[PDB]
Length: 71
Image (cartoon, rainbow, N blue to C red; front, side, top):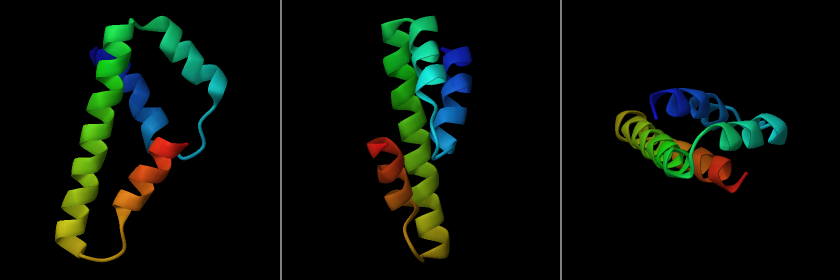
């Protein structure tokens, strides 16, 4: 789980995602851990976006999080 979340951090942070390496990550790690890694990455991303919303109070990084999830 630690290695999988470390790997999926790169995919989550970057808008451009390569299907080859993403399928490679899916294949490498178990379904339980793949789902867990996606959930942890999404939770952390939403929390950072919400903290930035609370601090700056301008624009919407949550829109970026939604766009990444849509991609």
